Image (tube, coloured by chain):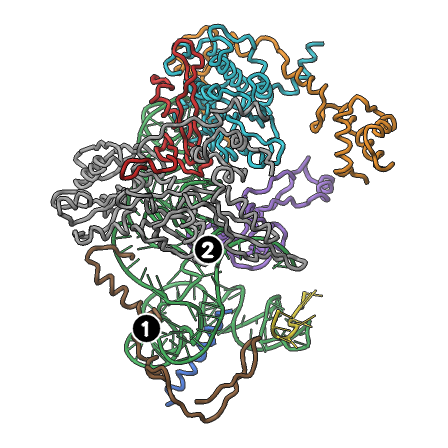
Chain colours: A brown, C red, D purple, E orange, G cyan, H blue, I yellow, J green
Amino acid sequence: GKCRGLRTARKLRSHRRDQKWHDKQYKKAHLGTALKANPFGGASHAKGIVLEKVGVEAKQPNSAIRKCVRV
Amino acid sequence: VRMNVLADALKSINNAEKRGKRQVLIRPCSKVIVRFLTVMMKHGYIGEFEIIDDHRAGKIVVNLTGRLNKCGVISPRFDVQLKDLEKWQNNLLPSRQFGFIVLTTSAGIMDHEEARRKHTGGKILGFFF
Amino acid sequence: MQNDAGEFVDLYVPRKCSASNRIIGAKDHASIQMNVAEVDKVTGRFNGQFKTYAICGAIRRMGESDDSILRLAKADGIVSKNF
Amino acid sequence: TKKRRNNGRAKKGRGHVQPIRCTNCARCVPKDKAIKKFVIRNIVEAAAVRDISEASVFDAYVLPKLYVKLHYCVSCAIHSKVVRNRSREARKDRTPPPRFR
Amino acid sequence: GRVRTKTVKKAARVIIEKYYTRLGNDFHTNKRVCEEIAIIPSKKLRNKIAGYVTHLMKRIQRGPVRGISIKLQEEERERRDNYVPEVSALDQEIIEVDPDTKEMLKLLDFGSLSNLQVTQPTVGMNFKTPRG
Amino acid sequence: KEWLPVTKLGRLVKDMKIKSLEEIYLFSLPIKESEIIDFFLGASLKDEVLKIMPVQKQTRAGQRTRFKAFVAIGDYNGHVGLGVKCSKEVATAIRGAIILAKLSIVPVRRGYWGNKIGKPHTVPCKVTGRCGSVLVRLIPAPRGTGIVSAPVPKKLLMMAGIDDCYTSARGCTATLGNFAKATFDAISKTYSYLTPDLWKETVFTKSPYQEFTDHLVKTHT
Amino acid sequence: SGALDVLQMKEEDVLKFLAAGTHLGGTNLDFQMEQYIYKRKSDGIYIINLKRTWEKLLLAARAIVAIENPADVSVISSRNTGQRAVLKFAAATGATPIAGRFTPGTFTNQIQTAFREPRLLVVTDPRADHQPLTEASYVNLPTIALCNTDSPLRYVDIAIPCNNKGAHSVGLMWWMLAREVLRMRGTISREHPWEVMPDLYFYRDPEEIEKEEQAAA
Amino acid sequence: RAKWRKKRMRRLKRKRRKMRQRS
RNA sequence: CACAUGUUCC
RNA sequence: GGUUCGAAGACGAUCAGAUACCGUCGUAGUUCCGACCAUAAACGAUGCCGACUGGCGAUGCGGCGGCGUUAUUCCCAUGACCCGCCGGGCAGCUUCCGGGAAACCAAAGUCUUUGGGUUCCGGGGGGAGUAUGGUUGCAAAGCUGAAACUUAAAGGAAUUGA
């Protein structure tokens, strides 16, 4: 790195501890706020009940009417 | 300021080896430095050296040949055992055809190939290839 | 380059520059052999033998070519030692 | 993308100098950044030099002169057509044009 | 309002190089000389080249031409390049020799010379152009 | 088919006076004729078109596109090279990369690893090559491992006959133009890097121009 | 060359350099020729050592005769000051001349008519002949350049310090070189001086050509 | 110009801080 | 001294 | 205390619209002192110390020596020029040193031939320097500082047309 001593280990991994949070992959897997916001809640499949049907207008040139469902 | 006596010595001679000088002037002379090049005397990588042994930090003038492409300095001085003398050469040396890792031990400053013989590793200095 | 048993396995041995004491690459397009004629000690005329030298292209592109060959020819006695 | 070594200014160790006002406009430019034309000017160009001579006091009276140090900015010098845009190979040529006429 | 192009100039020059001896000075004199020595497609093109043929000899009559290869001029340049002057100005009896050039000769093999003249050193060693 | 010689070293090929192309790369005289490699080692010289890529130029009237082909050449014994050609047609761009690929062959160094028994299988030392932002390294490998590298530099490494290879790269390797030529500098560095085996000073053989200068003025201009 | 009893610095050559103005240098200095300069005289002029001129002439004259074929040795003088000397050396020694207006591509284009592969190159000065030195790094060609105290030493293999500016000083250089290269090869002896005068190689201004012709008539 | 892209957010903050004290 | 703007896909 | 200039604001012209550019004013301000705030494209967009590596012409400080010129003319000695050099001070030209993606740089070089020492700081673009919390300030505001969500792009250098 930038500091190159022999007993700088606390200078080393504390200067690697806090920008691990600025990495998105480490922050996502260790901050539970998105885990709370995960509507699966740690799952992969979920049952659902329909209340209406919603037609979604598509994007820029590739345009159509998309069949979407309120769940 | 001046932190290392051996790192600046190898950087000064590598700055002139790419240029092609035959005689250079290195500002320090340490106990480690004067017997550091004696390893290259037994390996024939650099020509014979003359020093100015005075009441100051002496100046060493070494004869320059082309046999040493680059001598490397590592900072700081990591500890090396014989459970990992094969470990560094996988990332540090070009091969076992040539390339040398030098170490300073209780036997003295000495090479990894002969460190296998006397069975003593330890405090390390650098590598020349 | 020779093997365990002692046979030269390399397909050629590359040249060496005599100034910087380093080898010459296969695609070095500026390396030059200096061909120096031999002068007889009593006749002064051409003999039939040479004192060949070599210079690399990097020394040419900084400008230290002639200073080296003067030093190279001093050791071989071509340049006068009194100077 | 960087265009000059010194970016239109002749400041290398100052950091801060005294601004000066321009001439064509009132543009506030630092002194070592504006173009300083020390224009030399005779009072009458071609017309009255013969006309003063027939109404002067002494024999071959010498005419006085004006010395004003103009300070044009970047936009005011190009609007007065003094400086010119140059190729990047010819930008480094900072020698002044000669004084042939 | 007339410029000789590349086609006219390449046809006119090669005619002069090979057929110098057959050309004259008036335009009409060598105009029909060019008729027999080349295959000219049209009446106009023959008169176009031959004017520039006559235009170049006025350059030749003025003096030598850069882009031409004449055997006679080549021999005349060899006659003047191998011209022999009188005795050399390298071997004189009077030679200006600066004070600082003696001690390099004095420490050499021939210290004392015969036909040399020691000169005065120039007092005041200012030799550089003013700045600006 | 009937070759007319031009270059001075080119005449030396047909006179049966030079034994191999190794003496040319001893003296490193430049090569401009493309049949000399065919003459000596044109038996197993194998061609391969890497890729086609429609590079384009924007013009005032319409659009303007010309192609570009990449070729790795060699026999499976020490000699490989690279060829680059950007031409209008895919046929001429492919042959242009074929025809210049002879002109830029660099002999690689095969060396031993540990014991020196058998055949030289790997790179003698750790060397790298520099061009653009793509980095590549020739790392020695143990016996019987193979060319452990990306598929495009994998092809150029078994293209020379060097078998055990280890690599370590950095950069936008998707630009394989900058990635193939990075190996080219690395393999060319072996004959520029000084070896402790090659501390023996080289006796200077006399140049073939100097050796055969009598014949160089009697059979041509 | 080195301490050779046949090849000392000669008395009859002493008077030629002093009258010509060869030992005088320029106002400035190039960093390369520290060993080739004795001392600085008055009014900013350097002094070029004659012993260094003799020795570097021999090493230059070693390589000329070492190439046993003089038919493939090229000579360049793009400046008009060395024009007259070098042209007739092609006829005398056997060389191939490059006398002004050099064409780029003569060493890389196989289609050009003037496609050459010589063995040795002769340069009157590196500044006017920098373009020939460019292709010297692409094809392996030795060169000689007559260098001043300010001339660059880029892509120059063998260099001889002298004055490449004065008219009387330049034509002395090729004449003495021609007088030497004839001595190593078995054509002309060494005890007797050469019959041909050194004035034959001095470039003459066209002002004096029409003026000396007046003295003839 | 990005200078008043910042100043637009600055007017939003003064408006948003004033409704804090109203409650 | 003024001159602002030319609806989306290719 | 307000000379000049000049936010806000007013008036006269242009505009289809000026709440703008132009001109006439003109308040806070711009000037000084005592208390605040600590933001700038605070830029060399390039942290600090230290060894080495192209020359070249300069300039400034101090020191060394020297033909000579000019004043104290009345010289020793001091000054001003000229020649070099020494440590560094802002610097400048060239470049196949070398680096870089290139523009370019003698450092942005000594970097896969990877480690001289050390501080601050970034991890795709937005959301966002935002919410909240704490803290300084009379205030404007400053410092620290998110998340949900959204996107297959955002961006830098370079070539050619327009």
Q: Chain of mark 2?
A: F
The chain letter for the residue carrying disc 1 is A
SS for callout 1? helix
Question: Percent position (x, y) of residue G126?
Answer: 51, 30
Q: Position of residue C11 (x, y in %)?
A: 38, 37
Q: Can you identify the residue that label 2 sits on? A: F176
Nearer the observer, disc 2 or disc 1? 2
Nearer to me, E75 or J81: E75
Identify the amino acid type marked 2: Leu
Q: What crowding class fits label 1: few (fewer than 14 Cα within 10 Å), some (14-19), or many (20 or more)? A: some
Residue F55, relative to residue B15: is it above or below?
A: below
Q: Amino acid at mark 1?
A: Lys
The answer to whether E12 appears left or right of F73 in the picture is right
Residue G216 appears left or right of G134: right
Residue D40 is tagged as none
Residue H22, how many percent across, how many down? 38, 89
Secondary structure beneath dot 2 equals helix
Residue I2 on image: x %, y %: 67, 68
Asked which quadrant contains residue G58, the reply is: top left
* Image quadrant containing the N terminus of chain E: top right
Residue shown at 44% from the left, 10% from the top: G10
Disc 1 target residue: A27
Q: Residue at x 35, y 21 (%)?
A: C76
Name which quarter of the figure residue J136 lies in.
bottom left
Residue B129 showing in the rendered view: no
Which quadrant holds residue E114? top left
Given residues B118 and E126, the one toward you in this image is B118
Q: Residues within 10 Å of mark 2 (few under 14, many from 20)?
A: some
Q: Is residue F56 left or right of residue G31?
A: right
